[PDB]
Amino acid sequence: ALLSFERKYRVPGGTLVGGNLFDFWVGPFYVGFFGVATFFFAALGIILIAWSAVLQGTWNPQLISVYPPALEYGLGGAPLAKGGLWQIITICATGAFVSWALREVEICRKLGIGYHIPFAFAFAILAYLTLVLFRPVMMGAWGYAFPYGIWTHLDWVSNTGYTYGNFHYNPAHMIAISFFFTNALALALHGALVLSAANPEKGKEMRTPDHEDTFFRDLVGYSIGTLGIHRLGLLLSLSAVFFSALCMIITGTIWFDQWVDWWQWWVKLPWWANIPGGING
Amino acid sequence: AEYQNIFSQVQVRGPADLGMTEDVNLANRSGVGPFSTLLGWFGNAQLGPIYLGSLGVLSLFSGLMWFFTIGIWFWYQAGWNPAVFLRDLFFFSLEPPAPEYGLSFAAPLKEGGLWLIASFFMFVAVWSWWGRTYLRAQALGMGKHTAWAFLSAIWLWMVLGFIRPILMGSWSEAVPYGIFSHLDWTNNFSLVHGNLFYNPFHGLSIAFLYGSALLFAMHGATILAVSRFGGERELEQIADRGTAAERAALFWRWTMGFNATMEGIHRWAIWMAVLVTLTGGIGILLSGTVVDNWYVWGQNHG
Amino acid sequence: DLASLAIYSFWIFLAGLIYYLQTENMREGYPLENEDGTPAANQGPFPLPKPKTFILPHGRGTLTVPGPESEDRPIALARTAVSEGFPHAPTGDPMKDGVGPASWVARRDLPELDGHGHNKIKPMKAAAGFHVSAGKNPIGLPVRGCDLEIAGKVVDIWVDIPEQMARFLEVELKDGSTRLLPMQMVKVQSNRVHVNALSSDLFAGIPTIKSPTEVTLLEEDKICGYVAGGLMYAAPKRKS
Ligand code: BCL
Ligand code: BCL
Ligand code: BCL
Ligand SMILES: CC[C@H]1c2cc3[nH]c4c(c3C)C(=O)[C@H](C(=O)OC)c4c3nc(cc4[nH]c(cc(n2)[C@@H]1C)c(C(C)=O)c4C)[C@@H](C)[C@@H]3CCC(=O)OC/C=C(\C)CCC[C@H](C)CCC[C@H](C)CCCC(C)C
Ligand SMILES: CC[C@H]1c2cc3[nH]c4c(c3C)C(=O)[C@H](C(=O)OC)c4c3nc(cc4[nH]c(cc(n2)[C@@H]1C)c(C(C)=O)c4C)[C@@H](C)[C@@H]3CCC(=O)OC/C=C(\C)CCC[C@H](C)CCC[C@H](C)CCCC(C)C
Ligand SMILES: COC1=C(OC)C(=O)C(CC=C(C)C)=C(C)C1=O
Ligand SMILES: [Fe+2]
């Protein structure tokens, strides 16, 4: 039930709500009030998904698909079978995601550590709400949100993207991708570096962090350092998600054309909009 | 804020660190560069030294030729006009030979020959850089993890540019050198192969790309959260577990039911990242060689 | 179909990979224990990994994990329930007893060394010639607790020399002795250093180091654990 070093940490205190009433563990899991709330939103949300699977007639998980209301409903309530389950499930999921984060805060308090982890998780929640709430509301219908199904939400991605031509040309989308790529790069590098120091060549004693520094200085002339690389990883991954939400919040709200058209603020500028030749002239 | 340790409050500076010696040929290290106060807020301020040697120079050189070959072609497309060069910079493209040349190196320069030449320099630049990542580790007595991880990225690039076009029988199947044009190429590739969303190695690849952002957010944040206990000193935490490593592990155990070790999280990390391009490579490799239409292939489940 | 073959093979690979990563992450903290310290009956579906050895640099010896673990310190907690899963309450003073958020681990009572074998962390007055290169220099500033009372003044910075990083403020108390404060737990302002985790009369209980020019791994855990424990246990004096 316990790690060998765990007992000295399992003390009372740190809860935001409920004092000591939910201050306990189940196996390895800490509960707390928000553990109870998480469970309740998750339980209900999973029931509704089952209820909806019954309405759909299948129990094949890769066919099940809960869609949101038709556009004609705009932003109003819809009947359960006609988009209303989607609405309720979205409420539950939001309840669960937010509860999960506040449970993490209670755990941070009990352990005496910073709040960076639930802070970072809030961006993933922000990104979810951008797709199911912020953007649909700004466009004026729930039906612009994505369906809850394994393959159908991929169709939604595909459909939404090609609505504005090649979505590659969205400039906030370019920025987001660059952070996703750079982040994978840095994660590989960070993992490799620590392991290569802790697990050196055969016949060698364990390396020091100075070897790590020396390795990157030799390789590219700069070492960001052990604190800096963790700062960087957090920065890269949150920025990738931030620009993701950004590239969608502006799509269909303040920009309605094919994104390749955006790039003419450059092509047809004053000093050269006319000079013959090249690709555009 | 109850200070978050994202930026340093105070910077301190001392003599440049010239680095561990081990078996490094010290003849090939530069001098040290200047300190950067700007960078010092976020990470280390020291710039340099760097290590060069034969492979580094070969790699730099060969990489510059690559850049130069593309650049000169772009100037050619811009009719040697600077204004047109800047206007259309992102629309310029160096294309591979057309299909009718197959895999021959017998295409005229302005029709795919120059692409072949660029690819040759690019090919030399990357592999000699790979040799370098391997030899720097060796000279310091380190494990070869960095070289093996880099090989995973090289794999996806080899598939896109060389292995798949050879298997398809045509250089025209490779990726052009251009900002917008390799984007158009990417779009077009998916359309031609019946929607890559239904390529399962492509879905796997996306799971690890997302998974990488997930994990590095988890881990970056975890280390900052316990830096008040010196958590970022992970090598010494591996050798002699401190309350930093213990609280980090209990945070996740209590949240999620299980946890990592200070060494072990880095094994999760290296695999999460390298699986992105390992799987992606396989997915591209299979497209048009084995599977023409992923959507249709999918509806038969295989 | 070769694509089918490939995707089924990769899933086989991925399961073997996960099993590897999980066992590899069981090198610390296992076997699991009952709350009375005896081995738990249910140890999970993954076996303990076979031992591996690190050869530590600078003659510091070898480390083999997994291996038999102790806390190697008395733990002043009482069980609060007959059943499994409830909090263990401090029996004494948790700040001083080092439990909960105030815990420390019995790390080696030796300083960490850099690559060259020198102490990794040094007071800046002993480090030629480090100096403050940007930001507010905190030397000579007053240090204030959460009770808004002055606890002492900053007399030096302890620097991580290879990383060229400030890690501790050394603070002189009214009685003339000094204490180390983790740089991460302080807020340097224009006219003072503010410390939220501690009231001014709790600074004295920060553990002391036995050498005025070096700090050991054991001491850093004791210092950091005690200061961080203030957030939970010194909250009553954290001014309305
Ligand atoms: C044909 C399709 C179009 C296109 C159309 C779109 C559209 C449309 C969108 C994107 C968006 C994105 N695209 Mg695009 N895209 C294209 C091509 C590309 C290419 C490429 C190689 O060509 C790349 C690299 C990308 C990359 C990306 C990212 C920048 C971004 C998705 C990440 C994200 O938002 O995460 C954000 C993270 C989340 C949503 C995760 C939230 C998780 C929540 C909080 C918690 C879940 C808990 C879970 C249920 C619990 C289960 C627990 C149990 C224990 C199992 N696109 C083409 C041109 N792209 C999307 C975007 O930016 O969204 C904001 C988007 O909507
Ligand atoms: C981000 C921008 C787009 C989008 C674009 C894409 C694209 C494009 C792809 C996926 C893929 C997937 N997406 Mg999606 N996806 C979006 C929003 C979501 C949300 C959400 C609540 O916001 C969820 C839970 C998912 C979930 C998933 C998984 C089914 C799958 C692997 C993701 C992964 O490993 O991530 C990283 C996270 C982890 C590695 C941790 C584990 C996460 C587990 C696996 C989540 C399982 C969810 C579960 C099946 C559903 C709920 C369980 C409840 C009990 C009912 N997507 C939006 C709409 N997503 C891929 C796919 O289908 O592959 C076949 C794929 O190609
Ligand atoms: C219409 C567009 C298509 C599509 C078409 C493709 C194609 C085609 C490909 C991908 C690929 C990928 N796609 Mg897709 N993609 C779509 C939609 C998405 C969505 C989404 C939310 O909609 C997402 C998240 C993704 C995500 C992803 C990634 C998981 C994957 C790229 C991995 C990587 O790191 O490459 C970046 C890394 C590399 C290319 C390796 C580079 C290594 C070399 C050595 C670097 C050399 C550097 C050089 C020397 C120096 C250069 C400096 C520069 C000047 C900056 N795609 C839709 C369905 N996608 C790739 C893949 O693997 O697919 C299976 C791929 O080829
Ligand atoms: C912001 C940077 C990245 C990020 C960070 C991040 N995610 C995090 C954290 C952090 C720091 C956590 O602390 C937290 C965690 O505990 O992880 C172990 C979490 C987490 N990120 C998760 C998933 C996830 N993160 C993703 C992405 C990202 N996470 C970003 C890339 C994705 C992607 C890209 O698709 C996914 C799938 C979980 C593993 C976990 C949060 C777990 C949680 O919230 O649990 C409470 C909820 C439940 C137990 C179930 C609720 C069920 C619903 C009521 C019903 C289902 C609704 C849903 C809409 C169905 C739709 C599925 C279809 C789309 C297929
Ligand atoms: C595991 C998957 C991830 C990954 C891993 C990875 N990449 C790696 C490594 C690893 C582990 C290394 O060890 C290696 C490295 O050394 O990193 C510091 C590398 C690296 N990955 C890099 C890039 C890179 N990785 C990418 C992707 C990823 N790499 C994946 C997400 C991407 C993309 C497209 O997403 C890029 C761009 C390099 C920084 C480096 C490999 C260096 C190399 O091969 O260099 C040889 C080439 C040169 C020296 C050329 C120099 C010439 C100039 C740069 C000019 C070119 C400019 C351009 C053509 C412009 C033209 C117009 C003008 C005329 C105006
Ligand atoms: C010793 O600390 C360092 C790392 O830790 C793993 C790095 O990854 C890296 C490299 C990662 C990036 C992308 C700079 C550097 C430079 C570094 O100094
Ligand atoms: Fe790390």
Image (tube, coloured by chain):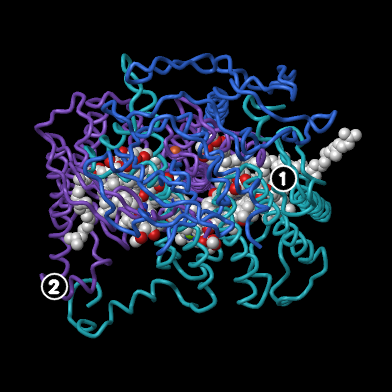
Q: Quadrant of residue B141?
A: top left
Subunit under mark 2? B
Residue type of the residue flagged with mark 2: Pro
Relative side of A143 to B164, left or right: right
Q: Nearer the viewer, residue A194 or C140?
A: C140
**Residue drawn 18% across and 43% down?**
B120
The answer to whether the residue labelled 1 contacts the one labelled 2, judged by CB atoms less than 8 Å apart, is no
Chain ID, cyan in image? A
According to the colouring, which chain is blue? C
Residue carrying label 1: A13
Instruction: Left or right? Give the position of A16 relative to B16.
Output: right
Rendered residue at 54%/77% (across/down): A253
Name the quarter where the C terminus of chain A is drawn.
Answer: bottom left
Q: State the image coordinates of residue B58 (x, y, percent, origin top left).
A: 13, 39
User: Quick one: label 1, few (<14), some, or many (20+) residues within 10 Å?
Assistant: many
The spot of residue C216 in percent (x, y) is 42, 29
* Residue B298 in view (yes/no): no
- Badge 1 marks a residue whose secondary structure is loop
Tell me whether marks 1 and 2 sit on the same chain. no
User: In the picture, which chain is purple?
Assistant: B
Q: Nearer the viewer, residue C19 or C77?
A: C77
Q: Is residue C84 left or right of residue A230?
A: right
Output the chain of dot 1. Answer: A
Query: Which residue position holds label 2?
Result: B82
Label 2: element kind: helix
